[PDB]
Image (tube, rainbow, N blue to C red; front, side):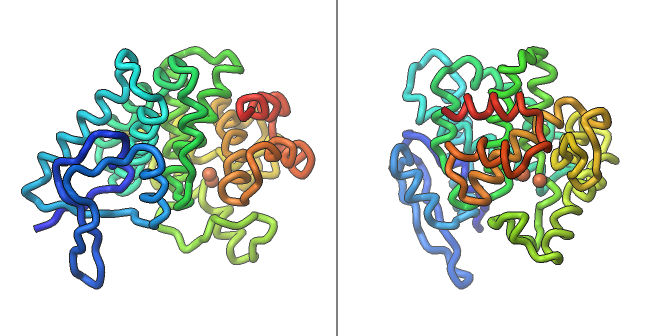
Length: 305
Ligand SMILES: [Fe+3]
Ligand SMILES: [Fe+3]
């Protein structure tokens, strides 16, 4: 009777041609009403509620799904000169959505290639628009979800990739996709990420240390998965002085996973540890001395401001 949708797919200024319900005590409350839109402070109010899921009437699906396609279509369109926060709203939420599919459907070959394909679209979107990054960085991770945090890391990762003069589209594409999915090993996990790793109980820290090794075990076996991606998923907590979980050093890694390992260190601070954007790079230079290419750290410092 009802079909669930992910909230990150409701973005931008197009008025909806369907109603959307949230579930309370097994009943479906009508929350979002026909003609509603989500541009501006609307998206914040919408995210202040920890709604991961909403629902639509099985006979309003086409309406919704048509809405979603037109949404992403026109958002990638570089021509329409539509507001950049607006386009960024739509695409960030869409990248976030694609990563959730793969996370819940990692064996689904077709989901993967959609995400991978979208990854490419995102790169071309980030490079080809000056505003993009600062606009995508406006959308907070209020929920603190690994899917949104993975969109954030991929974003830092692209900008970083550009500073380092990494240009191969197959590579920025594969880099982004693997940053997006980078935390799949946290998926369905008891661990509360919203704390600092120093303030972690040994029961948490040891549960945290397992996540790259486990996350990678769960996908190295699926032929449709690129190896760069498996590597990124498996290696992104590794640090150049080998203090990360597997204890790898720069020689042992995917170069692209070093680059992701740095872009992740930044957002764990900003998002999971409440360090203000401006001081994250500094925190790392001092309290995380040795763990990351200082050049990476420097560039990310620039990117932020
Ligand atoms: Fe991680
Ligand atoms: Fe992470």
